[PDB]
Image (cartoon, rainbow, N blue to C red; front, top):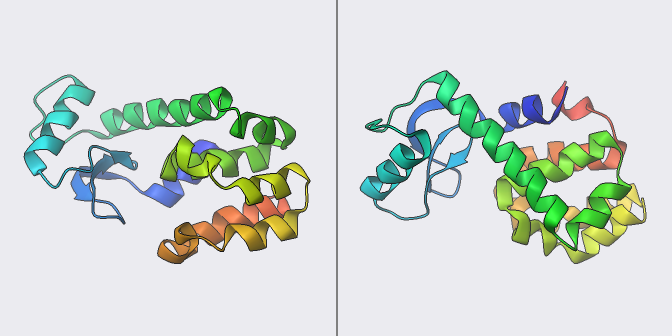
Length: 162
């Protein structure tokens, strides 16, 4: 298991524009196109992201290309963020993947706001961090995925993705 396979499990693969769990136009492996309610705006973002007139449909290779860019961007966001970087650097590789997963789903600024959870992770108080992470809109709106990510933080294993 690795961050790419973990996110493929959590995000799926769809080759036509679809609405994500929040109702926002998305394609591929959880590539958010826009929060605009305009499908035309989403189609314009997609063509810009892919570099051709897609008419709302992409190939698997194209979806994987955006996915690799999006994972890269999530990691970059962590490393440039004054609050996320020290936590990330303190973690082992498995728990690092859990943090990348959160940033992929909610964004750098969103995860950086989890001040008390981040502190508990920095302190390696894993059960306490897991309890705190679940007191969140994130957990309530996507509980099955949040449970997998939280288990990964709690145990430092891939058990929840087996």
